[PDB]
Image 1: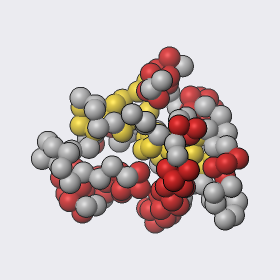
Image 2: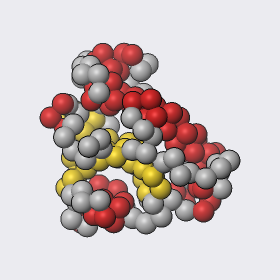
Image 3: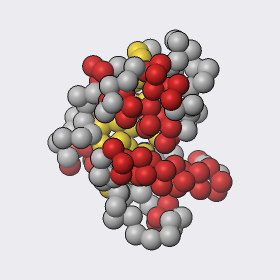
Length: 167
């Protein structure tokens, strides 16, 4: 019943080797968070390729990995709508989004991920995280974004509270 939290590697080849290594770090940290709240398998990595997998020190059976497009992963799991965390979104993430079955928490680079998903028939809810209506103090790292969502979704905390706690 719990949603997937997706790290989308669509833009993998546009990153430096250091940025690739930071993504692997964020995957490990995000698994740690979801292993506490849930089981850990709710973390899903799409466009997972061999270079990404070789940045780890063991198999990734504990998380959901998927070599193909995010839209295909969603369709395989009967999901037709996702929340895309995007600081340029018009609407702020809220409790009315927590019935959606998948949240894309990483992958945006600035061919937009949201445009490609919509062209493949996936409804995309673009939602931003703010603090007092501003971005000051709002973390932009994947695992911290995830921590904010989980505090709101699991613990029922307001966004201001969740952002403050995750600073």
